[PDB]
Image (cartoon, rainbow over all chains, first blue to last red; front, side, top):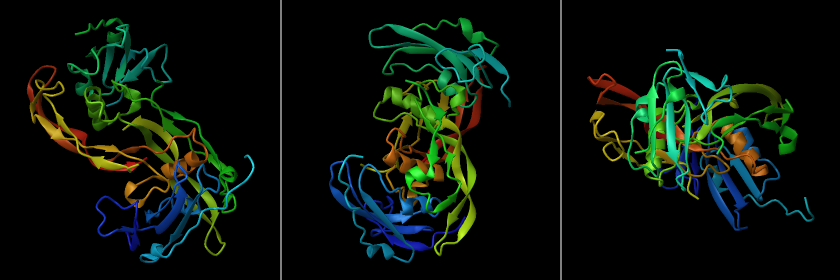
Length: 93
Length: 85
Length: 104
Length: 104
């Protein structure tokens, strides 16, 4: 493969052996904001592998719950992401 | 080692069974289990060579009573009548 | 009740929103794996020892899950997609299509 | 609401049947995999493309299951046992022990 070279902050998605809320990866750091099943909104962050990253960083636009994911690719860059919920839709669909 | 043994199957058939038979390199089995009313039920098929000895050996006091018997002969399994412990 | 097998799933890029970064193909047959892993695990479920051992443990201690039905071989598909500066490139995405399932 | 990880599990042979067909050991540490596969699958979950795609589809169509938390690396242990002729035999057993887990 291609070796991990990137260091990201993590919160919620930390590996189980994470040291001081950081993680390493050959992919991208991310931050994500979303409503859970109760409409509670939460902010979590971490590392994404290189393989599959096009799909996850782009997201699908209309999932069951509102979310927004953002990715960046420089050391600890996800401490600066401030992603925001998509505007809400009115009317059935 | 290719598959070489032919077994009957019922309840445990692969979607491509030929006249209710499967083909394997392990063993034919049959097994009788017991539901919650005691109204029991009898199924059979093919067991892979790998881990066959784990699945053929008989283990007491599960959630249920059941018994399983294996063998390795063409249709050995179509008239195997296991009996509950 | 119905046990571990492969099932059809077609993934249409424009229904999921990806059709403005994926120029080709418009979608593809991804399939998926789902279904029971009962005891015993018959041959065609290609369990490993571990999944076998664990299926037995689950019949004595239900606090420990059944083996799960997941892809056991996968194939690749190639795509035309945009890059950063709006260049279309071609690449071979590994592990996109499920070719077979098993209890693991 | 806790993610895919490996979890401890000791399998005691006497305690499950095979007390008397397996001379050695009496048990072994098997471990097992369990936990959520959420969107996004992080790096340490070693997901395939298929699983990443499937997670996105499940988020838009809930009839399609999430990926499952399963062993992605297994190792062997050898055992001493008496067989179908009943000779005492040393044998390597493949894929007995869960070394790590992922969303597949």
